[PDB]
Image 1 (cartoon, helix red, strand yellow):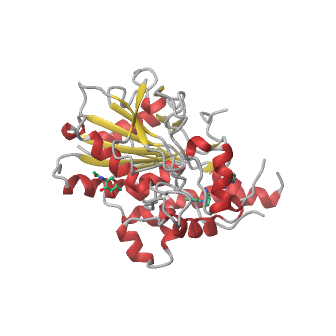
Image 2 (tube, rainbow, N blue to C red):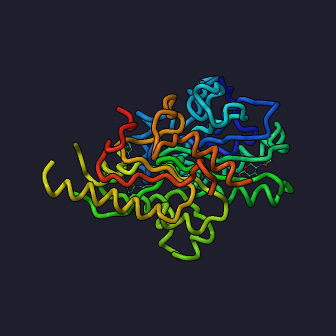
Image 3 (tube, rainbow, N blue to C red):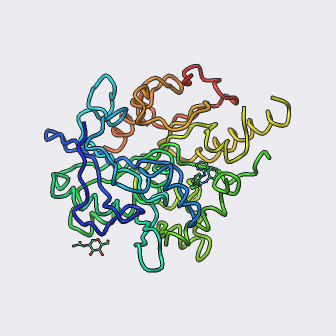
Length: 347
Ligand SMILES: *[C@@H]1O[C@H](CO)[C@@H](O)[C@H](O)[C@H]1NC(C)=O
Ligand SMILES: Nc1ccccc1Nc1ccccn1
Ligand SMILES: Nc1ccccc1Nc1ccccn1
């Protein structure tokens, strides 16, 4: 189990002003550190966030968090469950800022809620440096869904933080799972019906921050562009491995697709082709032709394969590449055009 630590700086808070925190399992024989960002959509105005506080309060508050959590998937210490990094130091950072990990705004006389996701990541890193992270060789910032987009928004800031604090030997890398979306035409709840508005409004509500090189490309008012992987990824300097199902369930929900006649068949095939196209120049990626959402902390994440290579193997090959490799690929994108045309897709 990973044990809870509430942040010592109690001014870095979840939405309702309670302290943020992290769950930690130390591995003193390892110089590898995995920091995983939880997902779970977001909220973008007073009324929307009030609803989330009634029925999704663990995503807005630490008041009811458990003492411990079990590591699963890439967070498991069992080699049978985690062929990739079973001996690493494991950190789970709960998502309690409702801001896709972008916010830097405190509660105040003018703000009902605090949106501090970007500052929560900075403070966790900061406090871990006193608990052994100072001796790390690799810091892998990973995350799923909104946490996967959060990796893209924060990996270069963590790298800059560690350089400025005097730790230039720690190699910062990112792993973004199910956080790579298309701002495409829909097939036919504002957060699902009108996604780009929801992001634009959220950024202003959260005082949200995007990576500087991307911000400079799109300029004032157009920061929402940097929440889309194919637009922010080319501006990043840290190595980033991208995991994305080609027919992602959250993408299809936003597109108003529910599972088929010709119009919908053509729409679904075109979505796979467009996602494939955006990954063509991403050298470290894993994109199976399946209808699903998230993978890296699922216990059976070992089962899916692309061209005969599993995701744990592809990540191991990526480690080797950062020291093409014969028999050990890092770029794995399905070419077949319909969900579950890959036999290893999950049921
Ligand atoms: C605690 O965090 C807040 C928000 O980032 C910051 O203003 C303050 O300086 C921090 N306190 C300490 C002692 O680092
Ligand atoms: N934005 C929000 C806040 C409170 C309750 C529901 C929603 N809507 C929603 C739609 C799809 C997936 C998750 N949430
Ligand atoms: N979930 C989704 C799917 C397809 C298009 C837009 C969204 N919205 C979104 C919100 C924050 C960050 C990235 N995307």
